[PDB]
Image (cartoon, rainbow over the protein chains, first blue to last red):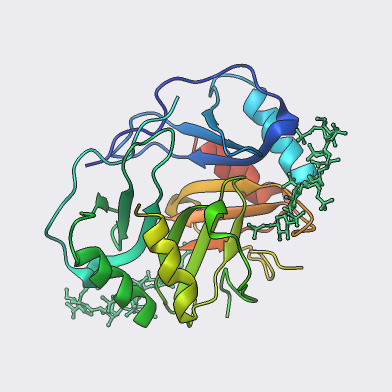
Amino acid sequence: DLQCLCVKTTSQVRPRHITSLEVIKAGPHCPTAQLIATLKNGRKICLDLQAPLYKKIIKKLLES
Amino acid sequence: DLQCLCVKTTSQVRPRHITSLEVIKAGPHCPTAQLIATLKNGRKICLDLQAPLYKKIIKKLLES
Amino acid sequence: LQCLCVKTTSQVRPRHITSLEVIKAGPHCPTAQLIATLKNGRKICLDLQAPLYKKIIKKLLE
Amino acid sequence: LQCLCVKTTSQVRPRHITSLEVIKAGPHCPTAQLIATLKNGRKICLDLQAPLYKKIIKKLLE
Ligand SMILES: CO[C@H]1O[C@H](COS(=O)(=O)O)[C@@H](O[C@@H]2O[C@@H](C(=O)O)[C@@H](O[C@H]3O[C@H](COS(=O)(=O)O)[C@@H](O[C@@H]4O[C@H](C(=O)O)[C@@H](O[C@H]5O[C@H](COS(=O)(=O)O)[C@@H](O)[C@H](O)[C@H]5NS(=O)(=O)O)[C@H](O)[C@H]4O)[C@H](OS(=O)(=O)O)[C@H]3NS(=O)(=O)O)[C@H](O)[C@H]2OS(=O)(=O)O)[C@H](O)[C@H]1NS(=O)(=O)O
Ligand SMILES: CO[C@H]1O[C@H](COS(=O)(=O)O)[C@@H](O[C@@H]2O[C@@H](C(=O)O)[C@@H](O[C@H]3O[C@H](COS(=O)(=O)O)[C@@H](O[C@@H]4O[C@H](C(=O)O)[C@@H](O[C@H]5O[C@H](COS(=O)(=O)O)[C@@H](O)[C@H](O)[C@H]5NS(=O)(=O)O)[C@H](O)[C@H]4O)[C@H](OS(=O)(=O)O)[C@H]3NS(=O)(=O)O)[C@H](O)[C@H]2OS(=O)(=O)O)[C@H](O)[C@H]1NS(=O)(=O)O
């Protein structure tokens, strides 16, 4: 009934452009964790789990 | 980067078992609208768009 | 009263809404909650009043 | 002050959390928002305090 939201991660986007980050735990409908980021223009993208980039994105959004 | 969350709809579930319903507009990452329902036990399922069932689920959750 | 929607809002541009989640009342929230997510990822609590969320759900279903 | 997280909470079972969304501050919300979604679909606003959301994000990443 449900699959993963993200097909492939991305590496390049400006942390300034990010308004929202959702962290989704692995579940019955997706074997891997997911990192969905929403941008000012409505564009949604996926981040890499094995990178410190998500750590940078998160640390910024909270600092705002 | 993103696909649809729901693969196939469902027809049978008890409206009593439903705690949350999310209505997702069609977008660049999914050609069709989506109706995701969350249940007390954590189970998530998709509803049918061409049915009055979603109308029943929604009308109940608000009445609660 | 430990709800997501303490104060609630009536003014929003329906075209800016990408999703609407209806969360049911419970021991922790006296009322149902209408959470709308906008294009920019932000969220706001919709007034449970009638014609507001009526038109929205249909515009999400087009 | 028309935020999702007016009042905020500190007591939640991390195993009950299925997702955590960080919404950034803006002209409409003075602070960033930590919205946690539980197994039963409900949502609660997490305290922006340190060790609460630190352990959670990692438990979501296992
Ligand atoms: C191209 O060069 C540019 O370089 C950088 C990068 O640009 S980027 O950010 O676009 O990538 C620019 O730096 C940014 O400059 C500002 C900007 O983004 O415009 C500024 O952003 C902050 O302030 C924005 C202006 O808002 S306002 O307060 O001055 O009015 C704000 O964007 C506005 O958000 C409001 C809002 O959310 O309330 C919007 O208001 C409108 O919608 C509201 C909500 O609608 S709803 O549907 O019901 O929900 C309505 O209630 C309201 O009536 C309505 N107002 S109206 O005017 O339409 O009538 C409005 O449309 C938006 O423009 C930013 O909000 S945010 O959501 O994007 O975060 C806000 N960001 S903040 O800094 O975090 O507070 C910053 O200086 C900077 O943005 S950034 O976030 O730091 O990246 C640079 O300005 C620009 N150079 S330029 O070429 O000279 O322009
Ligand atoms: C098998 O036969 C059954 O038939 C029907 C159908 O069952 S079904 O609903 O499971 O499908 C049963 O009818 C239901 O009966 C009640 C029930 O579901 O148990 C009742 O539901 C309402 O009340 C529940 C009991 O709560 S309590 O207030 O009395 O304490 C409630 O479930 C509890 O929710 C709380 C909660 O959300 O706060 C939970 O508390 C615990 O977690 C909290 C939050 O954690 S968090 O992670 O931090 O977020 C903690 O804060 C708290 O400390 C902790 N308490 S503790 O006990 O663990 O220490 C608790 O775990 C839950 O059990 C229902 O909440 S809900 O979220 O499911 O909606 C609530 N539903 S409500 O009616 O909408 O308010 C109803 O009568 C009915 O449920 S229903 O929603 O109408 O469908 C029937 O009882 C049963 N017959 S039986 O065989 O005899 O049992």
